[PDB]
Amino acid sequence: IGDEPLENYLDTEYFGTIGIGTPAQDFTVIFDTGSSNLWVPSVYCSSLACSDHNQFNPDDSSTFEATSQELSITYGTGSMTGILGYDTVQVGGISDTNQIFGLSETEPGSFLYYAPFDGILGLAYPSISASGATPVFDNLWDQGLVSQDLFSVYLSSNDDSGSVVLLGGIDSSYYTGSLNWVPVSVEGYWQITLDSITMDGETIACSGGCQAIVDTGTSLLTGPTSAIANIQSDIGASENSDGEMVISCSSIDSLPDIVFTINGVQYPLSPSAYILDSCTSGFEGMDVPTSSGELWILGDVFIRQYYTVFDRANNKVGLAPVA
Ligand SMILES: CC(C)CN(C[C@@H](O)[C@H](Cc1ccccc1)NC(=O)O[C@H]1CO[C@H]2OCC[C@H]21)S(=O)(=O)c1ccc(N)cc1
Image 1 (tube, rainbow, N blue to C red):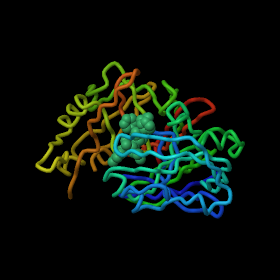
Image 2: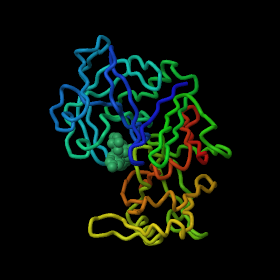
Image 3: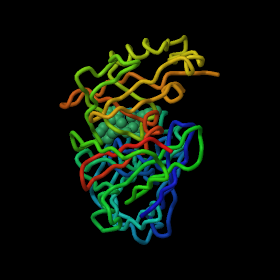
């Protein structure tokens, strides 16, 4: 069982340190349950974001093995191109030998330039991995480096230490109540079916059910723009001169919970959770069309309240209230 500590950056990004190569070269990476590739910047990249982050040098690693395979990835915000290579990745105390990963050759745009992390370590299914690159957790399981084919995530609140990805384990000191299990509706993301979203007993969005993904790599709780607009109006959030969804901090003590029903079980978010003396909404409209329908994203606003188990043996997500 391996523990990967995560730094809680402003309650907005959660990244941990990994080592790549022999001797290890260290990188910070977002542990991203919304994607499946591992990549870091490399000495082959001249983009600005490469210049202001740690760059992998395969020349200095005695265990590196080159490939002729290229890689390209476009995220919601940010993108990269590069080349795949193999090396040993130290992650959570585990020596992940023979791990394929991306060495960036371009990283355009300001988001990656201003972000504190060097790269991204995806934790989702192989079906959405660019170039069919084996995801880290698949390679761990393939090599028997974890005995149980699952991992769990605790994300801390209030910029506190203690966030972790627990590779191969579930730890009940991080939660209370019973874990409830949700089948993965479509294997790619950690995608699940939401039944309803309610406030003070009435349905405010997702009437008749909708699709959602559980994504540590997204800060906010996002949904289709039209639905989110209603929710913003429902909680009293107004966009201001600067493009921020502003809300009176006094509503934190006024407003009722917003309740997500998932597989028939109610998961409340208190206004303490879905309102971030500058208070803004934890919701954001973002349209993610798929053959499944538009996706909602249960990002860190949600995951901070629910210890989450990602079970690849079973293709299920487990949820329980954080301790
Ligand atoms: C780069 C990540 C650390 C951040 N992203 C979260 C990530 O989970 C998204 C979450 C996501 C998912 C779907 C649509 C938009 C965003 N996944 C994603 O874009 O996956 C990509 C992998 O290759 C492609 O195939 C799947 C989608 C692409 S992100 O949505 O782009 C993002 C970027 C900036 C901020 N501030 C907040 C979120």
